[PDB]
Amino acid sequence: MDVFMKGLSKAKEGVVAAAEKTKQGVAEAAGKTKEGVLYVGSKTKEGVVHGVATVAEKTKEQVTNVGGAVVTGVTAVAQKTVEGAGSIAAATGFVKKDQ
Amino acid sequence: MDVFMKGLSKAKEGVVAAAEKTKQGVAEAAGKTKEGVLYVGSKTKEGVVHGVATVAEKTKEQVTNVGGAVVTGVTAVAQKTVEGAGSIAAATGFVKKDQ
Amino acid sequence: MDVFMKGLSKAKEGVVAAAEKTKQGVAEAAGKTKEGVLYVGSKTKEGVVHGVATVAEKTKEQVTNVGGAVVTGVTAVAQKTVEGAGSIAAATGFVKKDQ
Amino acid sequence: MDVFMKGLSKAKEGVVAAAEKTKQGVAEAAGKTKEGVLYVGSKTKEGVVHGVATVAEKTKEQVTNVGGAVVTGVTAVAQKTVEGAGSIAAATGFVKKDQ
Amino acid sequence: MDVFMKGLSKAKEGVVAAAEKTKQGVAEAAGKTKEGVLYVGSKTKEGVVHGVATVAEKTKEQVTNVGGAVVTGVTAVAQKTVEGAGSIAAATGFVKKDQ
Amino acid sequence: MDVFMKGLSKAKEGVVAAAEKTKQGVAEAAGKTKEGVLYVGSKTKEGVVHGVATVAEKTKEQVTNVGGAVVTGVTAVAQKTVEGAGSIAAATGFVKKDQ
Amino acid sequence: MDVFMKGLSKAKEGVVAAAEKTKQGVAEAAGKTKEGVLYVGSKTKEGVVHGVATVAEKTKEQVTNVGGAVVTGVTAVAQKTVEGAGSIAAATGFVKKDQ
Amino acid sequence: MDVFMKGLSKAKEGVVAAAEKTKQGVAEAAGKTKEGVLYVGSKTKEGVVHGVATVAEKTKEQVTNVGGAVVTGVTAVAQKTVEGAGSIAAATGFVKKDQ
Amino acid sequence: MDVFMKGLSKAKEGVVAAAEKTKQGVAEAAGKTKEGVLYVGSKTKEGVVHGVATVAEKTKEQVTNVGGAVVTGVTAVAQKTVEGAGSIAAATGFVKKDQ
Amino acid sequence: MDVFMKGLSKAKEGVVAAAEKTKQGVAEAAGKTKEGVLYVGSKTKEGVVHGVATVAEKTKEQVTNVGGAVVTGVTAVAQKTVEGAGSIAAATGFVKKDQ
C-alpha cells in the first residue's frame, strides 16, 4: 500500500522530475510596508514616506512645492527572456528506448 | 507500505530530479519596512522616509521645494535572460537505453 | 515500510538530484527597515531616512530645497544571464545504458 | 523500515546529488536597519540616516539644500553570468553504463 | 531500520554529493545597522549616519548644503561569472561503468 | 473586548469557583497492558499473564490443573461515600449580602 | 482587552477559587505493563507474569497445579469517605457583605 | 490589555485560591513494568515475575505446585477519610466585609 | 499590559494562595520495574522477580512447590485521614474587613 | 508591563502564599528497579530478585519449596493523619483589616 505524492511507484524505468516554486528569467519586485507583523497590546504611531512629505504635528504654515518630478513605486520588467535559439525548462523528464 | 513524497519506489532504473524554490536568471528586489516583527505591550513612534521629508513636531513654517527629481522605489529588471543558443534547466531527469 | 521524501527506494540504478533554495545568475537586493524583531514592553522613538530629511522636534522654520536629484530605492538587475552557447542547470539526473 | 529524506535506499548503483541553499553567479545586496533584534523593557531613541539629514531637537532655523545628487539604496547586478560555452550546474547526478 | 538524510543506504556503488550553503562566483554585500542584538531593561540614544548629517540637540541655525554628490548604499555586482569554456559545479556525482 | 473562559468580567462582587478534573471519594482502578506506546520499525514478542499460565515454545505435554480459585481483574469499590450529616462539594460559590 | 481563563477581570470584590486535577479521599490503583514507551528499530522478547507461570522455550513436560488460590489484579477501595458531620470541599469561594 | 490564567485583574479586594494537582487523604498505588522508556536500535530479552514462576530455556520437566495462596497486585484503600467533625478543603477563598 | 498566571494584578488588598502538586495525608506506593530509561543500540537480558522463581537456562527438572503463601504487590492505605475536629487545607485565602 | 506567575502586581496589601510539591503527613514508598538509566551500545545480563529465587545457568535439578510465607512489595500507610483538633495547611494567606 503506497501513499505518495509527486512521484511514482512500481514503474520500472521511472523518471520523476518535480519543480516546485521555481523561477527562471523572473523579475520580482516587492514593496511592502508591513509583512507578517504581530501587535499584542501595543500602541504605535508609525509613519512611512515614499516620495516627498512635509510632516508636522503643530505648525502654522506648510508649503510643498513640486516643480520637478516625484517618481516612486514598485517596478518589475522581464524583457527578452529567451532571445535566439534559447531554452528554459522546468520539470522535464523522459525515457528514451530507441532501437 | 511506502509513504513518500517527491520521489519514487520500486522502479528499477529510476531517476528523481527535484528542484524546490530554485532561482535562475532572477532579479528580485524587496523593499519592506517591517517583515516579521512582534510587538508585545510596546509603545513606539517609528518613522521611515524614502525620498525627501521635512519633519517637525512643533514648528511655525515648513517649506519643501522639489525643483529636481525625487526617484525612489523597488525595481527589478530581468533582461536577455537567455541570449543565443543558451540553456536554463531545473529538475531535468531522463533514462536513455538506446540500442 | 519506507517513509521518505525527495528520494527513492528500491530502484536499482537510481539517481536522486535535489536542488533546494538554489540561486544561479540571481540578483537579489533587499532593503528592509526591520526584519524579525521583537518588542516586549519597550518604548522606542525610531526613525530611518533614505534620501534627504530635515528633522526637528521644536523649531521655527524648516526649508528643504531639492534642486538636484534624490535617487534611492532597492534595485536588482539580472541581465544577459546566459549569453552564448551557455548552460545553467539545477537538479539534473539521468541514467544512460546505451548498447 | 527506512525513514529518510533527500536520498535513496536499496538501489544498487545509486547517486544522490543534493544542493541546498547554493549560490552561483549571484549578486545579493542587503541593506537592513534591524534584523533579528529583541527589546525587553527597553527605551530607545534610535535614528539612522542614509543620505543627507539635518537633525535637531530644539532649533530655530533649518535649511537643507540639495543642488547636487543624493544617490542611495540597495543595488544588486548579475550581468553576463554565463558568457560563452559556459556551464553552471547544481545537484547533477547520473549513472552511465554504456556497452 | 535506517533513519537518514542527504544520503543513501544499501546501494552498492553509491555516491553522495552534498552541497549546502555553498557560494561560487557570488558577490554578497550586507549593510546592517543592528543584526541579532538584545536589549533587556536598557535605555539608549543610538544614531547612525551614512552620508552627510548635521546633528544638534540645541541650536539656532542649521544649514546643510550638498552641491556635490552624496553616494551611499549597499552594492553587489556579479559580472561575467563564467566567461569562456568555463565550469562551475556543486554537488556533482556519478557512477560510470562503461564496457 | 474581553475574551475569556470559565470566569467573569465586569460584575462587581463576582465569584468564580472552578473545579476541573476533581475527584472526591473516588475509587479508580486501572489495569492496562499498554497505554501510550509507540513502535517504529520494531519487532517484539511480548506476553503478559494475569493468573495462571503454562507457556512453552516447543514441548510434548502440557497439563494445567486448576482445582482451586484463580481470581483476577480490575476492581473498584466506592462504598458509603457520605455517611452521616456529611458534605462533599466542588466548585461552590456564592455572594451573601443580607441586611 | 482582557484575554483570560479560569478567572475574572474588573469585578471589585472578586474571588477566584480554582481546583484542577485535585483528589480528596481518593483510592487510585494503577497496574500497567507499559505506559509511555517508545520502540525505534528495536527487537524485544518481553514477558510479564502476575500470578503463577510455568515458562519454557524447549521442554518435554509441563504441569501447573493450582490447588490453592491465585488472587491478583488491580484493586481500589474508597470506603466511608465522609463519616460523621464531615466536610470535603474543592474550589469554594464566596463574598459575604452582611449588614 | 491583561492576558492571564487562573487569576484576576482589577478587582479591588480580590482573592485567588488555586489548587492544582493536589491530593488530600489519597491512597495511590502504582505497579508499572515500564513507564517512559525509549528503545532505539536495541535488542532485549526482558522478563518480570510477580508471584511464582518456573522459567527455563531448555528443560525436560517443569512442575509448579501451588497448594497455598499466591496473592499479588496493586491495591489502594482510602477508608474513613473524614471521620468526625472534620474538614478537608482545597482552593478556598472568600471576602468577608460584614458590618 | 499584564501577562500572568495563577495570580492577580491591580486589586488592592489581593491574596494569592496557590498549591501545586501538594500532598496531605497521602499514601503513595510505586512499584516500577523501569521508569525513564533509554536504550540506544544496547543488548540486554534483564530479569526481575517479585516473589518466588525457579530460573534456569539449561536444566532437566524444575519443581516449584508453594505450600505456603506468596504475598506481593504494591499497596497504599490512607485510613482515618482526618479523625476528630480536624482540618486539612490547601490554597486557602481570604480578605476580612469586618466593621 | 508585568509578566509573572504565581504572584501578584500592584495590589497594595498583597499576600502571596505558594506551596509547590509540598508533602504533609505523607507516606511515600517507591520500589523501582531502574529509574532514569541510559544504555548506549552496552550489553548487560542484569537480574534482580525480591523474595526467593533458585537461579542457575546450567543445572540438572531445581527444587524450590516455600512452606512458609514470602511477603514482599511496596507498601505505604498514612493513618490518623490529623487526630484531634489538629491542623494541616499549605499555601494559606489572608488580609485582616477589622475595625
Image: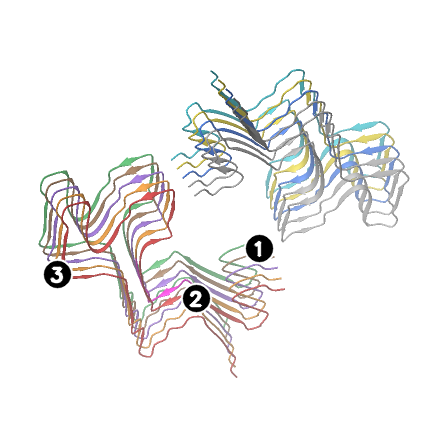
Chain colours: A red, B orange, C purple, D brown, E green, H blue, I yellow, J cyan
The mark closer to the camera, 2 or 3, is: 3
Tell me if residue I4 comes above or below residue D91 in the rendering: above
In the figure, is residue E82 to the left or right of A51?
A: right
Q: How many marks?
A: 3
Q: Quadrant of residue I71?
A: top right
Instruction: Magenta stretch: give its range.
Output: B20-30
Q: Are marks 2 and 1 on the same chain?
A: no
| Disc number placed over residue I2 in the picture, else none | none
Which residue is at 54% across, 57% downward?
A: D4
The main secondary structure of the magenta stretch is strand
| Secondary structure category for the residue under label 1 | loop
Which sits in the foreground, E52 or B65?
B65
Q: CA distance from mark 2 to mark 3?
A: 54 Å
Which chain is mark 3 on? A
- Residue with the mark numbered 2: C91
Which chain is mark 2 on? C
The mark closer to the camera, 1 or 3, is: 3
Q: CA distance from mark 1 to mark 3?
A: 72 Å
Which sits in the foreground, C38 or J37?
C38
Q: Amino acid at mark 1?
A: Asp
Q: Are marks 2 and 3 on the same chain?
A: no
| Secondary structure category for the residue under label 3 | loop
